[PDB]
Amino acid sequence: QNKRRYRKDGFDLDLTYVTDHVIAMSFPSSGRQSLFRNPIGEVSRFFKTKHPDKFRIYNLCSERGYDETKFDNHVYRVMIDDHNVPTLVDLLKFIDDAKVWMTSDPDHVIAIHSKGGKGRTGTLVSSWLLEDGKFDTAKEALEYFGSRRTDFEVGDVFQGVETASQIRYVGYFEKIKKNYGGQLPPMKKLKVTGVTITAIQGVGRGNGSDLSMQIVSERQEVLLCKFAEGYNCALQYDATDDCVTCEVKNCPVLAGDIKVRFMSTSKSLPRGYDNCPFYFWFNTSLVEGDHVTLKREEIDNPHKKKTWKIYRDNFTVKLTFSDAED
Image (cartoon, rainbow, N blue to C red):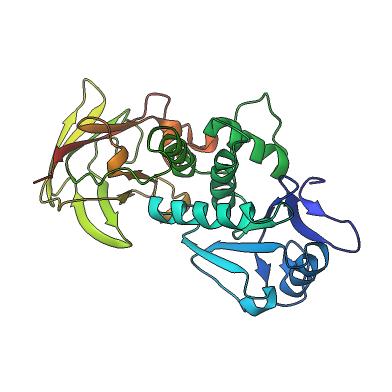
């Protein structure tokens, strides 16, 4: 916790200099309370005294804003839901905004914040560190963020802080910078035609009968499948292989950033983040072949070790696609 709180020069804030010019911090909260929160008046005072006319604040909270005149109108908003990811368009828009600001003056600083300054903040700080060339791999940037912000040490396995999708999206940016020259990859239109879950035993009813699947595009449900009932689908349970395979029916053309949520009627399947047992994000342009397969540690919620009694080491989810291009 010594890395967590800034305690110098009469300040007391959950604020971390990730580098000399890159700051990660928690939400500048209303009121004067300072127990596990950063009072907005004090955060305003920090940047006005320590970085006068040389700061830019990034608010990554879709859920909450504030009076941005308190920061002299130097606030940029990225609308990210807690425990989720920015769109690739929004991530790249942020990256360009940061790069222009940082290039004009060596003494300029960026302060990225979310609610706790963990997952969402780690997503954009790691992406920026790749952009600025401090690291060439997403893994290296993320682990460095963990070492500065949390009690993580470089050498041990990377766990906590970011979600699996948040990790994936930093990886997406690396691929964008390396293979696409920092440009958004060409639009790819797809339709989901099947879902396959392995190691289904012990997951809810253990045969897919409790499960439902929601596809979300641009903050709207575009499809809902209910497995046992045949609601926009056709479930098959393979007891011998310990797997379920489900034909996905009536999926509309999907493009961009897609959120897939799996829900259960069975209460014996706990809810982690996002009010469901498991979920994930992917971008259609970054899909390779006719499928995407995600291991346990690549899915949001099972990526946590506390759930590993239910989601085993061979638990995977695979989406099969069809080409929706003209």
